[PDB]
Image 1: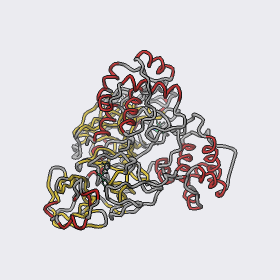
Image 2 (image 1 turned 60 degrees about the horizontal axis):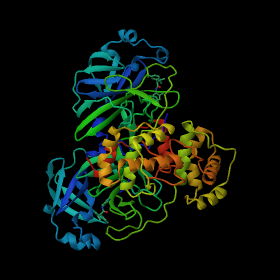
Image 3 (image 1 turned 60 degrees about the vertical axis):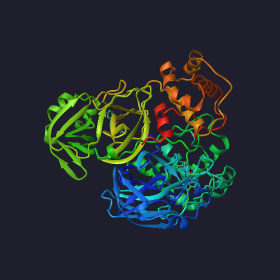
Image 4 (image 1 turned 135 degrees about the vertical axis):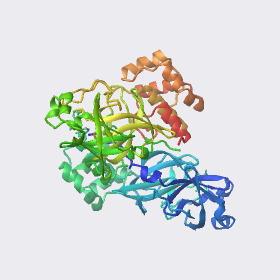
Amino acid sequence: SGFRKMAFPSGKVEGCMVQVTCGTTTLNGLWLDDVVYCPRHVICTSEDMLNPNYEDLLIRKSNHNFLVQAGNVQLRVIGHSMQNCVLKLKVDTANPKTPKYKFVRIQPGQTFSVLACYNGSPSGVYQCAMRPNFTIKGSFLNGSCGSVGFNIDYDCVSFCYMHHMELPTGVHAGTDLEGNFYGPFVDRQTAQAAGTDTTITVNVLAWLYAAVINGDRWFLNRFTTTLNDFNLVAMKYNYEPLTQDHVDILGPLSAQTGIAVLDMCASLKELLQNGMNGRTILGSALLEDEFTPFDVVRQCSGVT
Amino acid sequence: SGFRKMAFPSGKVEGCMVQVTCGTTTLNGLWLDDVVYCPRHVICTSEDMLNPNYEDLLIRKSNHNFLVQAGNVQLRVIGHSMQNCVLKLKVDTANPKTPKYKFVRIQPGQTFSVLACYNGSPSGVYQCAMRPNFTIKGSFLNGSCGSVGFNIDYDCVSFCYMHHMELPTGVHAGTDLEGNFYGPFVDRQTAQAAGTDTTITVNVLAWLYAAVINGDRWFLNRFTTTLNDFNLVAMKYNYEPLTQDHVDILGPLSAQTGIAVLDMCASLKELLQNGMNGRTILGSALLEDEFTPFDVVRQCSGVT
Ligand SMILES: Cc1ccncc1NC(=O)[C@@H](c1cccc(Cl)c1)C(C)C
Ligand SMILES: Cc1ccncc1NC(=O)[C@@H](c1cccc(Cl)c1)C(C)C
């Protein structure tokens, strides 16, 4: 009973958080095996951020300039390299708390948990989605850079995001663990605007299935629709177009509830055209799009 | 930038989760030092739950009937006792992962993180509030009993909740770690109805302060009000009455934003009387009441 915006347990990732200082700048690092991953803008001063030349700035840095601290103990840095927008600091000690892990580059619409950190210490955990415009709507302050996004399957942590920046509109941009930004963002203090933040249609449908499973059924109607008819409505409301791939992924939820995917699409269509009329769905007065079909199944079945 | 429903990092609590089996029933236990805490209904069969006599049922149980498993290793049970609605199983090994901890009984309106578990294994973490009717709106399935609610200050985990049951309306009831239920609930499979779920006014005001801090200011108006005038409106909308104690607790947020508490009360009054008019506040189309004034300060300052 009940449906909550649930994050993965953060323990396995807390044991990886370290603090990295280079000169006057301090941010977070992810320590996996004998490597510490961090945003390359740790080498920049506030003035450098306006138009940094990272290759040139990195020439003035040696292994001893990167101060890595895990808890209250200092790690010895024996190598350093730049991979896209991240620095990989080879230390002399493998992290004894390294969980089973993978580096994954997620697609927009996918969700993940963020362990927000400051000075290598965890402050909190929350659930995010990679928006269709490749930004994330997080909660990050100065010092939170190097905080990571991740998913967990059984005992394996799939790291997918590393926080780098905030756009002037209060949204967040970052990279995967190979240092490649999601979207067209650059690690420079320059005005970078986000594109249209469209709604993740398949996630909304998944959340409507979660609602039916938990007893909120008022929005179920007598109508059905087609993929093409639904998508005409989706385009109008800035919703992502729904494909047969999205329909396939909703299969298990459709099977459990007995409500055909296209019937749920017709309920969503009426919700878009008429609104909620002052009503709520799973304690929300808007259509929630940051639960994937996999998140709904996991939460509704008790996957540990 | 940004404001999220953030949970505390769960690692310190993950290291405490164990599985407890008694006969055919399996639920979660909290292992702190050499004691495992769990709901006393672990001794019940499905038939027992209708009208259990826990003292009588416990007579037929010995130390060897409580199977405690931490990960994949079995703990030896050397003592057992019932304290209110929890069982305290003395084991022969102190939990090496026991964090600094306290047992606190929270007041309604206070928030906490829940580490939902099944079979001693963590499934996810989310943020809850103790409702004014002493229920919590969680996400729990069969097997989640024994999952705990907690807050963290620096390195000390304050455990405040242990999950016991779901009411027929899909809301949740449980105890503090001394086994005392929050509210009037009993650990019996009997129809127990919740009272009015009133809105936590001080939390809504705290969240409006968080919104102003993050740039959502459209709801700020030219009005002010008094505690008595505001409370006439609060009574009408099933909001908790606001006291000078609530005003005092909002002091630091009032000081940071420069918006007097009674002015923010007048904005909230207009929001209650006029609605949102299709607009959003911090990505929400309703007035969020599960952030305390302390949660807003912590998130807005970066407390680790
Ligand atoms: C202040 C903040 C709040 C939340 N998240 C991150 C930051 N940090 C920055 O946005 C930094 C930044 C700007 C532009 C590009 C890059 Cl790579 C980094 C810096 C301007 C302080
Ligand atoms: C099924 C579920 C889902 C979510 N949270 C808890 C449960 N568990 C119960 O509600 C149990 C229960 C009922 C009445 C009293 C007590 Cl102490 C325990 C039992 C009826 C299965």
